[PDB]
Length: 209
Ligand SMILES: NC(=O)c1ccc2c(c1)CCCO2
Image 1 (cartoon, protein in one colour):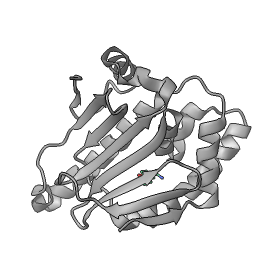
Image 2: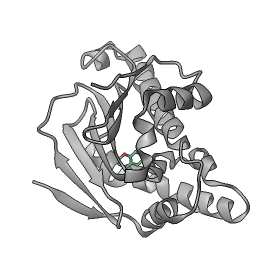
Image 3: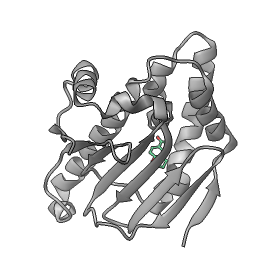
């Protein structure tokens, strides 16, 4: 059973801007997703200090980067706090509305797209390089869900029947045809070293084949 939702108009406008604006420095998408993963890992780690059972779904706190040239996907996996169905449908878009407005005014005042993370909407930088984004997520308090959007104003949510994750978030970037450089090991290593060198969780870059 697949549910289809409309983005809020302001979020649809942000995604169109990200997709349509000429902006060569696309590699910052990875910094934003890794930073999002680090934030999610901070949250479950802090919650586990007063409720150790919150780690019954997985003790390991890490980030995995998985390229797949056959599928042309780059997957960012973390074992963070995960995301509820209400997060996917309502809560994140509510917070994103005010950050999008602030980001919009900042851009007209001279800011650039690489500053997107300062406004809490860095996730949408994924559409700098991805024609479609699939998000698999599991929060301790909810079921495992699959969120998906190719932009165009709508997204879907379904219960995920795939491999159980235990806890966390998997962001699957279906890359645009001219953005396959982000499947190369040397390119990903360069970006992580440049932008994410002090993340306080192990980042493992998987090797292809
Ligand atoms: N607004 C945000 O910062 C955000 C983050 C993650 C995320 C979404 C939105 C949409 C659902 C899938 O995952």
